[PDB]
Amino acid sequence: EDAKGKSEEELANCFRIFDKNADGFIDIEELGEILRATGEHVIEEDIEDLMKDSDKNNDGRIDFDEFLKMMEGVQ
Ligand SMILES: [Ca+2]
Ligand SMILES: [Ca+2]
Image (cartoon, rainbow, N blue to C red):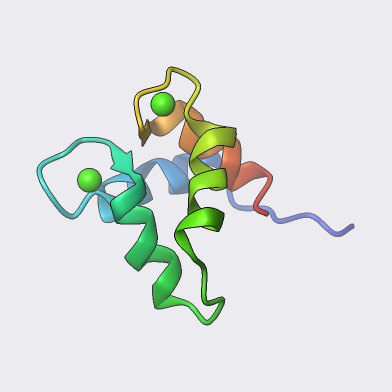
């Protein structure tokens, strides 16, 4: 289904672009605005699922490992 190209390197940097507050980790609260900014009208019930597929250590926060994992398979 076509290739996305890009590479982990680029995504790596984006990491800091997500953590706009002293957190060093992406939590659900941050996911809200992030997704809300787009035109998908996401609701907590949906944003929560995104964290589940990522949160591999039950830390209520997506890190670089869990984050990249999702970015690779968006949606
Ligand atoms: Ca953060
Ligand atoms: Ca986690």
